[PDB]
Structure formats: C-alpha cells, structure tokens
Amino acid sequence: MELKASEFGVVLSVDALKLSRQSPLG
Image 1 (cartoon, rainbow, N blue to C red):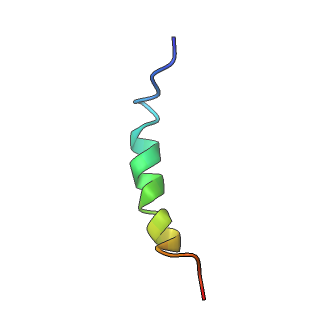
Image 2 (image 1 turned 90 degrees about the vertical axis):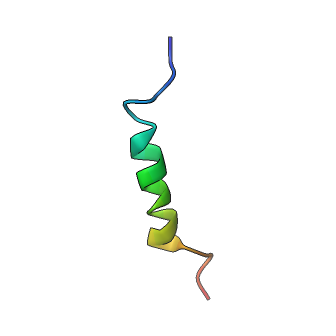
C-alpha cells in the first residue's frame, strides 16, 4: 500500500526544480 501518484506530480514538478538547479552550478 504505497504508489505515490497524488505525490508523483509533486515529483516531476520537483524536476522543474532540477531546473531550479538545471545543472551542478559552476
């Protein structure tokens, strides 16, 4: 009993925050 999908959109919009990053700074 698990399968985070009411938190999987929290995930790929967190990936928009891997754009928050885009790429390991300098």
